[PDB]
Image 1 (spheres, rainbow, N blue to C red):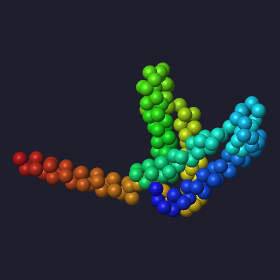
Image 2 (image 1 turned 180 degrees about the horizontal axis):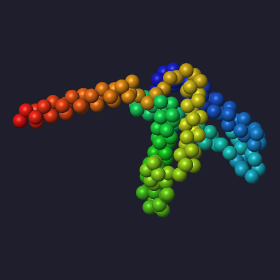
Image 3 (image 1 turned 120 degrees about the vertical axis):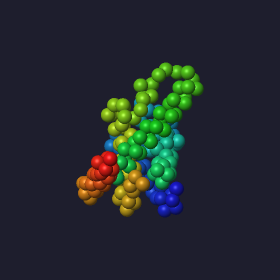
Length: 167
């Protein structure tokens, strides 16, 4: 957790709260201490106290995985991490309670497109703000080099052939 990014965490939390506020004012949500869903009344204007910070909490964790591990590659890796953390939580709870089998208990290269899009949405949401703030992030000629490698292999083969023809 870098110091300047730790500073920016609060500002990004505020910006995401403002975006969700625009969404909830488009939908219709007025502040009210009583908890309800059919009455369209919530005390944090259906995001509760902890529910408002559920998505803010793993931003720092995503940053730590970023540091511990170009742009599309980071997006797909962050999506993979978003699915891996949820898969670990789900498998842990199902092993704890001995429940049913979830169709999401499969490697990420098999999932349906919607299951990957769901986490890719949040991934791009957090990445666009990192891009606007000037944070250059990555994962962390070719034909000519290939031709050179081929030439070296050919030289080795020629050495071998000379050794063989010497006999």
